[PDB]
Image: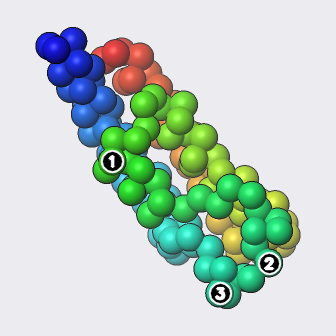
Amino acid sequence: SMEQVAMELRLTELTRLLRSVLDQLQDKDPARIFAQPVSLKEVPDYLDHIKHPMDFATMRKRLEAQGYKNLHEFEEDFDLIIDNCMKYNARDTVFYRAAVRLRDQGGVVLRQARREVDSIG
């Protein structure tokens, strides 16, 4: 149907906008602390602590499969990156501190992404 095509064009355009959002958020992590999944070989207890691991590469795979239906879904995954790090790692660590800075800086980007998603539809 033409209705299904129109819906798919909308998902494709959201995907474009979320790709640019993702690139902007990832630039706020120049250390690349959040680029890749936590290694279970290097942190074998990780899953005892963290139930839903998340990282930018995993978000990128979901994105390219057009697997985010709305901005809320994307934000949930970004929040997991931050929140997982802040639980596993202590306040005095470079990892925790990197997550705070990512969250603070990411806030700016996400605020305008929500306006653009509402504004464009």
Q: Which mark is residue 75?
A: none
**SS of the residue at dot 2?**
loop
Residue lying farthest to the front in this orientation: 1
Is 79 drawn above or below residue 11 in the view shown? below
Label of residue 65 in the image = 1
Q: Quadrant of the N terminus?
A: top left
Q: Nearer the viewer, residue 97 or 118?
A: 118
Asked whether residue 42 appears in the rendered view, the answer is: yes
Amino acid carrying mark 3 in the image: Lys
Question: Tag 3, which secondary structure?
Answer: loop
Displayed quadrant of residue 100 = bottom right
Residue type highlighted by circle 1: Ala
Q: Up-down: is 95 above or below 114? A: below
Q: Residue at x 57, y 48 (%)?
A: 78
> Identity of the amino acid at label 2?
Asp
Disc 1 crowd rating (10 Å Cα; few below 14, some 14-19, many 20+) is few
Q: Position of residue 109 (x, y in %)?
A: 47, 40
Give residue 45's mark.
2
Disc 3 marks which residue? 41
The quadrant of the image that shows the C terminus is top left
Q: Residue placed at 76% from the left, 62% from the top?
A: 50
Residue lying furthest bottom in this view? 42
